Image 1 (cartoon, helix red, strand yellow):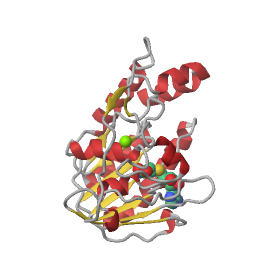
Image 2 (cartoon, rainbow, N blue to C red):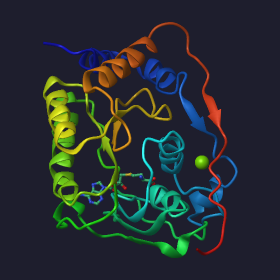
Image 3 (cartoon, helix red, strand yellow):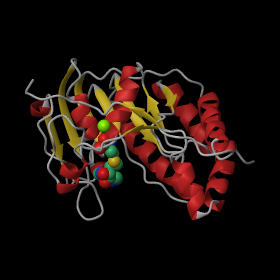
Length: 260
Ligand SMILES: Nc1ncnc2c1ncn2[C@@H]1O[C@H](CSCC[C@H](N)C(=O)O)[C@@H](O)[C@H]1O
Ligand SMILES: [Mg+2]
């Protein structure tokens, strides 16, 4: 019983290195992030330049009402902190706590002074899967590493989803959770069951590359799982045909400066 997403995964794996390369950015939405690129690679933040592409992904969802962060924000798997620092600029957000693994193969928090930096605390060296859940108003989680195997992507997603369940049981009023693999029938059933229990819906963020089927389970969406997943699968499959399309650019994120 093969889904569209599984056919996309199979075809993605059949691509030559050149085909994959041309495909992965074809027609996507993008932020250029030229302008403080060397500063970031040096490990010094510049003003209100975002520390990662993640700020733009969160911005895209917030600008469209897919969630309205407020109160105490928890950011699981914060990496460099792009989500935490974007959240700190939202008027109703009061406090941001980010946790991430860091160390060798992994992103360390970047320490910056974009607007609202002083209500942000990011901590490295923590395994979020070993943290007991805690009350919060806005729950964010951006964890899930890609794999050429769909069974692996699926298993990795189910572990993430089991982990956030403890946090959702605390009943945050807003959330945004990356779903690395939504495209197997087991995943779709699991996601429907989670939406029945916790609400929200799945959204494809168009700044995601075509090389990942990731979607975001967000409290401000209402979507049908089959509709949102199948539409994404069909978009990704369609971009495999025909000539390569250019990227569409948004304005770089500007998180300003100053305390709150
Ligand atoms: N068990 C775990 N505990 C803590 N962090 C983890 C983890 N598994 C993966 N991660 C971290 O989750 C992060 C996913 S990256 C998230 C991008 C971030 N939203 C931003 O905007 O910058 C990675 O840095 C990775 O190291
Ligand atoms: Mg940017």
